[PDB]
Length: 195
Ligand code: NA
Image (cartoon, rainbow, N blue to C red):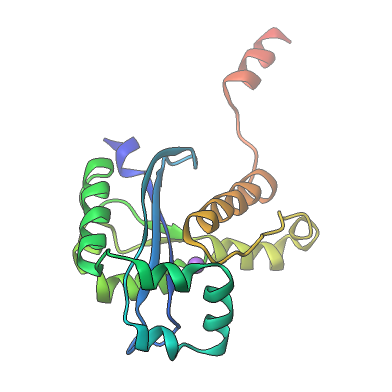
């Protein structure tokens, strides 16, 4: 019960840009962690077909970044429609999380949520409305723990979906281990008794 409801649905998307009125999802990856950030299951990792005209009119930033990562070429070759991709993700979360109870998780994952609410609404219906925004914790770390903030892991920032999920989890793990308060565990309790 509670353990299942405390899972997290980590997602990262690539889009043709930041304009919700025109831009589209071109890559999406998803995995599930338990409440303690251990990966329980790897979900689909999909490159979604979108029209040539849209890719050709992307911002210079997106042309450069999705170009050099290979993503633009892979979008043009993709046979995966948005609808089929959404189904794969929805089927996956239906196997992994109780309906309505688990949040999206990632860095500034509200941006992903904005695109998913519009373009994958049935996927989003399986999830809670709250999010685990790693960048909220980042912004609190920078303010409240400036010394510790300097030791956060460096990110490769490849703008590819699955690799970026792993970096997001690693960042949150860093904050848990370095700016949240310490707690008892099985090993410390056995030592306390032994002393
Ligand atoms: Na992202």
